[PDB]
Image (cartoon, rainbow over all chains, first blue to last red; front, side, top):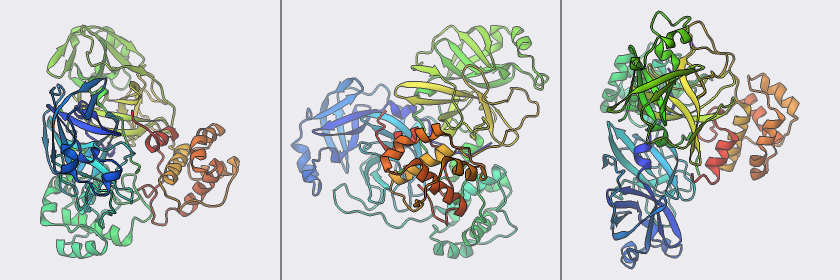
Length: 306
Length: 305
């Protein structure tokens, strides 16, 4: 019993974190095979950060200008290239700790674990959702640039995120491991602000199922609804439209509890309009939207990894 | 910036979990050097779960009654002894991934990370706190017995909890790594029930300071209170009483923000009286009590680690 927000065990990734230094700036890198991956704004200075010329600044850099430390050991750089917003440093040694991995790009609403690091050292791990405005609400202090987010499938690590910057509202923005930003952001010291966010409706439903699985059920009612009636209510409360697809991923939970998806939907729409009656669900006084359906299944059936 | 419920990286503990089987019972064990630790109820059968005589049960076991597997590999048990409610199995191989570690016993309000495991394999990692009724509100399924709680300050792993059982209310009870239960609980399937759970006041106050550090200000007021008057009010909301030691502990955060501890107590008292008015603090719509003053400092100022 019980239900916590839960991250993937981080061991496979802590073996990959290194420290990267270019002049006065030091940040984190991801050492896989013989390549170290890190944000390309490491080559920047404070002077040319309002308008970087990243191709221009790169070639002028020597392979020995980049200093890569893995713990007490130094890594010689024998080459570099830039892929979108990610720098790649070729080193002469393969990482003996490289796990099975693959680079994936995630969809808004999907969750992942973040390994926050500083000076190449893993500091903490936590669970984030890719918000619909393509930010994540993380916890990142100065020097956490280059920290990575990931999921684990069986024994394959899926790297989905690499941290680049903080937005003025305190939310965070980054790229996939191929250097493409999530959302309408750029890595320049310019003025940027996240779009308007929406509740990940399917995640709220999954969380309500997790509450029912755990015996927390005061919100269930006798009513049902349809996609059309629900969505008209959802827009006015700034909720993501519930598609036919969403219902089918909720299938397993709809089976294991005996509450149909449109049945659960009528409970959620009542909570939207009436409120929570000063009560809590799963020890929360707000509708939690950072648990995906797979997160609830993985946690309420005990999937383990390697 | 930002503030999240954060766990320690789990790699150092992942290298230590193994699967321990006795008869038809399988749970998790902790493999450090040449000892594997696990809950001693792994040696119970179904006839010995109301009033098990563990000394009697254990002397009847041979080393070959215990199957220990680290992944693909079988560990040969060469001895066994009992320390309070924890079994210790000596094996012929020290664990090559044993980290630097120690065993500590924690006090209520303290937080730690939990590496939940099944059949010796990690399923996930989350943060917990030891409540004042000496339970934790974990997330455990059947087969999670033997999972451990830990902190990693610097490079030393501090093991402070091993999971033994779930109580009829959904909460969990366990031991330190010396086999002593937290609280009045026993590893018997007899009727047991958690004492009243109080809100961990010093942690709430710490979280409110973390909010101010992060820029939240809407809940501040111009009142201050005495320590006695605050405890009279907070008691009525089932809050833990605040001692002078707690006031000292909040001193550093108090200095960093400029808000006196007793003046933040006045803010908490008002929040209990009016609730949140639909607003949030640090992303939450209730008052969080699972962050220590130490947790707040580590996350809000330099952590590195």
